[PDB]
Image (cartoon, rainbow, N blue to C red):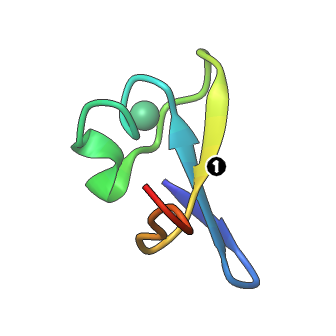
Amino acid sequence: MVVINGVKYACDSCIKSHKAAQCEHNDRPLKILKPRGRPPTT
Ligand SMILES: [Zn+2]
């Protein structure tokens, strides 16, 4: 996975899987993520 400033990211084959724990792939579409969030309502 990758992180910038205070943002997180990883391949769709990790962030969606779990390997993101230490993703280091190249190909494949990347994505972003953060330390939990949750909706404002539901
Ligand atoms: Zn990956």
Q: Residue at x 60, y 27 (%)?
A: 26
Q: Residue at x 59, y 15 (%)?
A: 28
Q: Residues within 10 Å of mark 1 (few under 14, many from 20)?
A: some
- Front-lying residue, 24 or 18: 18
**Quadrant of the displayed image that contains ligand 1:** top left
Which residue was labeled with disc 1?
32
Q: Residue at x 28, y 57 (%)?
A: 21
How far across and down, in percent of the image, does residue 35 sit? 44, 74
From the viewer's perspective, is 15 left or right of 7?
left
Q: Quadrant of residue 15?
A: top left
How far across and down, in percent of the image, does residue 39 sit? 51, 61
Vertical relation: 32 (above or below) 29: below
From the viewer's perspective, is 18 left or right of 9?
left
**Most distant residue in the left direction:** 18
Vertical relation: 26 (above or below) 21: above
- Front-lying residue, 39 or 11: 39
Vertical relation: 9 (above or below) 5: above
Q: Residue at x 39, y 23 (%)?
A: 13
User: What element does badge 1 sit on?
Assistant: strand
How far across and down, in percent of the image, does residue 36 sit? 41, 70
**Most distant residue in the front direction:** 41
Query: Where does the C terminus fall, quadrant-wise?
Result: bottom left
- Amino acid carrying label 1: it is Ile
